[PDB]
Image (cartoon, rainbow, N blue to C red; front, side):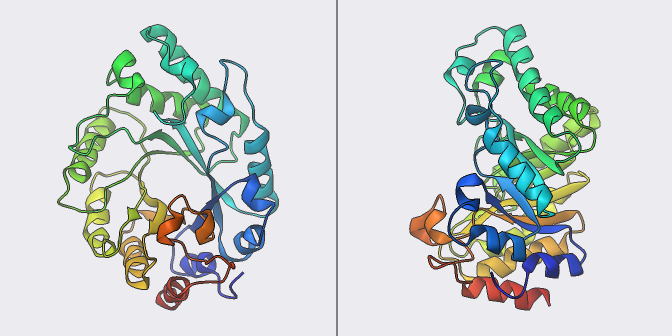
Length: 302
């Protein structure tokens, strides 16, 4: 645990939180729990709330891991972002085997409703639809799009709003880091259109999985995302290859510059546990010590 808390400091700047991804396996090992208790104010389950973990067989739900995280977060006063309801990856074979529209629609709605009701009122925001866009801006052809059609997105959001009206509903994606990139422009246009049609999309989540030097582009991309008119935008899965203080400070500044940016979530605590460990992209090193980038963020926020 670093003496200075980036969550406390970003709250003092007027934002809601600075959080991290975690789960039971991290919370019960090393210094993870201590670091999260002291330096962060929000948690996102890395895997425990995904479809494969929660509904491995239709109608046979498993909430053991999710319950652990939600209870831990509640006891320690941390906000929670549910992740993620509709996604083509980590999807059980029984789902992708369905070719009937009525069936898949009902299965999808039941999955959304069951997960959201269980934690009704305890989840700040949910990543309802994840990675629905192709790099060229068109919609990714997943089983949901192929079987249900474009309406699967409006249906997912309408169903989520009904299950828990307290939660902020997000569409989440990666490679929305450059204002000139087709994907960035497309999600803004589609979200504008969906909201105009009454679809309840409260926020756009930008994963922000960056390579060295890409932080600068976020200074323009984030305000562009905010122009879609959603109540909120957030940096949801931040990590930067090389963990340069320059890239990290640029991302934090981008959020500070955008009124609707509510917070930032970094994807993990210590480098070894990163999904991209070879690029040592996080804020704490292998020995759980804060890295230069962490200190740079603290200094930038003071």
